[PDB]
Amino acid sequence: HHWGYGKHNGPEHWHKDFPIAKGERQSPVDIDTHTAKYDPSLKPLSVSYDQATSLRILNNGHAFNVEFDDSQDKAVLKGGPLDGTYRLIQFHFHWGSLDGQGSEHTVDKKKYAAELHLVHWNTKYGDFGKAVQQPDGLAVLGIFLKVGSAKPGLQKVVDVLDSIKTKGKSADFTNFDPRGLLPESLDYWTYPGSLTTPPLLECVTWIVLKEPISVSSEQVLKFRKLNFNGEGEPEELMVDNWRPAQPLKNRQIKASFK
Ligand SMILES: [N]S(=O)(=O)[C][C][C]C1234B567B89%10B%11%12%13B85%14B%1158B%12%11%15B%139%12B%1061B%12%112C5%153B%14874
Ligand SMILES: [Zn+2]
């Protein structure tokens, strides 16, 4: 009886195994755009993905992860609200059963169809497992997805999904360029928060981009053909793999833009 997204094991149950679910800096949150304060001390974000080396794509039973070689400083995030250098380890998505839900963060209570998370760890802690034990250990870049025009840079991901339909399947996934998943603008909101899945550790500086990317209905429909179950098990479509907004508590969301 492991955690997942269903009504007997989903987000309202997670606190029993992970009591930090009811902590002081949980994610995601609703971004109230009129209350977020412009902070002129915030720096532009530096996203350096020119040397990113993807290796593999994995269906972990919750989502799919596109994994990178993080054994050297290649793909790094810096600037913005961050002190120091954060190395890209993986990306994944959260999405819905229908286009009206799927994102984890919300904007003035608006839910997007999906949300991309690019996960990076702070190199000053040496490895990812040490980073997640620190309040400034991770930086996750969050990008909203809306349904309209296709995202050409997403199509390589979409086309490999048939080969990782079920939990525990992986596939080689080299030379994928995550620059093709970024919007034009790097304007962002930022706040201190947590992982949005168990173990829910309070280790993340969230950077949520204001500009969504557009993906096609066909692209998101292929996300929704994945399975939460393993091969040879009854089919449970991989949809609605998002945690709802959590209480903001004693936090301020800052905006990089006027
Ligand atoms: N939504 S999120 O906060 O970016 C957490 C994504 C899930 C996981 B998978 B395992 B390790 B791998 B890394 B940390 B652990 B789970 B948390 C992030 B990724
Ligand atoms: Zn995530």
Image: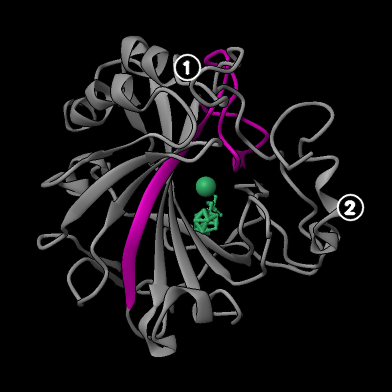
Q: Which residue is mark 2?
A: 16
Question: Is 236 within the magenta?
Answer: no
Q: Write down the quadrant of residue 105 in the picture.
A: top right
Task: Relative to 37, say whether 64 is above or below.
Answer: above
The circle on residue 93 is none
Range drawn in magenta = 86-112
Along the line of sight, the residue nearer the viewer: 128 or 231: 231
User: Looking at the picture, which amino acid does disc 1 mark?
Assistant: Arg
Q: Which residue is mark 1?
A: 224
Q: For this rendering, which residue is in front, 21 or 164?
A: 164
Does residue 93 sit above or below 35 in this rendering?
above
- In the rendered image, residue 174, in percent from the top left (x then y), is placed at 14, 46
Instruction: Name the amino acid, label 2.
Output: Lys
The vertical placement of 195 against 176, above or below, is below
Task: Tell me where residue 126 sits by quadrant.
Answer: bottom left
Q: Residue drawn 20% across and 41% down?
A: 172
- Nearer to us: label 2 or label 1: 2
From the viewer's perspective, tell me whether residue 108 is left or right of residue 12.
Answer: left
At x 60% / y 72%, what residue is drawn? 203
Q: Residue at x 69, y 37 (%)?
A: 4
- State the separation of the CA atoms marked 2 and 1: 29 Å
